[PDB]
Amino acid sequence: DLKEFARSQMQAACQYLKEKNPKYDWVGFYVLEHGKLKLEAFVGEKTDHVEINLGDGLCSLAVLKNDIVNEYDVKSNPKYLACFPSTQSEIVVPVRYQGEPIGEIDIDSDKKAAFSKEDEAMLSSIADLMAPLVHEFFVK
Amino acid sequence: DLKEFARSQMQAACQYLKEKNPKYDWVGFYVLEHGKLKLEAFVGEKTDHVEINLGDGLCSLAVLKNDIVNEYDVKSNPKYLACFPSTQSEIVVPVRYQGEPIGEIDIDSDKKAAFSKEDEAMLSSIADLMAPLVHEFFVKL
C-alpha cells in the first residue's frame, strides 16, 4: 500500500538518523491512530511499549502540548515512561500535518544530556519534511 | 545535511519504486534548480542527461504544463528525449510544492505501454508525499 512506501521512508529516516548520530541509541516514529500513539517504524532494540496510552510518557507530552520535549535527565521527570533500562536522555519532536500534531519522532539515548539545540533544530526540520509520509498512518 | 538527508530519502524512494515494480527500468528525481531540471537521485543505468534544458524532453513537458505525462509509445512523441536506447514508455509525474511545480519523478520502461492509471494514481500520491523533501533541492530565479 502507500503505507508500505511511507513505512519504507520512515524506516530509512530512522536509519539515516541512527547512523549519522551515534548518540542516538533508539530512533522511532510514533503515529496518532485512534487517539493512541502506535509505533510504525524504528531503528534499535525492540521497545517495551510498541503502543502507548495517551498520557503516559514524554511521548504523550510532546503531542498533547504540541511542543518539543528535550529531557536531559529522564530520571528527574515524573512523566518519563521507561522503554529501556539504560536511557538517560529522551527527545520527542512533534510531527505536524496542516498545523495539527499527528505523530512524533521519539529518540532515546543512554547518554545524559545527549541532545543539544542543534539536535532539536534538525529533528524539527526532519519532522516537517517527513510529515506527509507520517500522515499516511494517521487516524482520528 | 538537510539536503544530504533529503537525498537519502529520495534515493530510497527510487529504490523501493524500482523494486516493487519490475517494469520500472529507470526511476529518477529531477528538481528545478535555477530554471533547469537537474538529476538529484535515481536508480538504474546512468543517464547522459543529468541536466535538462527546459524545453527538451517529456521531462520538460511535465513541469511546463504542470500535469502527468504518460507516453506509452515514445517514438510517436516529438517531445520525447532519448536517454536510453531501449525505453518504450516514459512517465513523468510532477512534484508540486504549495501548488507550484518544483521537480518531477521520471520513470522509463523498456516495455511499451508500461504505465497504467494505477501507476499514474500511485505515483502522483507519492510525488505529493515527497514534495517537501524534494523541495530541499529547489531553487528559483
Image (cartoon, coloured by chain):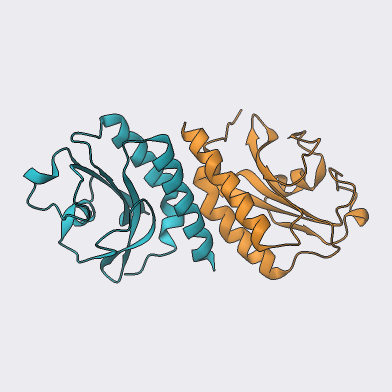
Chain colours: A cyan, B orange
Q: Considering only vertical position in the picture, is B65 above or below B141?
A: below
- In the picture, the quarter occupied by the C terminus of chain B is top right
Task: Kindly identify the residue that appears in the image at 84 percent across and 57 percent down.
Answer: B110
- Which residue lies at the image location 75% right of the left edge and 45% below the top edge? B59
Q: Nearer the viewer, residue B109 or A97?
A: B109
Horizontal relation, residue A23 to residue A76: left or right? right
* Above or below: residue A21 compared with residue A35: above
Residue A77 is left or right of residue A132, and the answer is left
Q: Is residue A69 visible?
A: no
* Residue at the limit of the structure toward the bottom, as seen here: A34
Give me the residue at 36% from left, 51% from top.
Answer: A44
Task: Where is residue B45? Give x, y as percent.
Answer: 77, 44
- Horizontal and vertical percent position of residue A135: 41, 60
Quarter of the figure with residue A119: top left
Camera sees residue B15: yes
Q: Position of residue B105 (x, y in %)?
A: 66, 49
Q: Nearer the viewer, residue A99 or A7?
A: A7
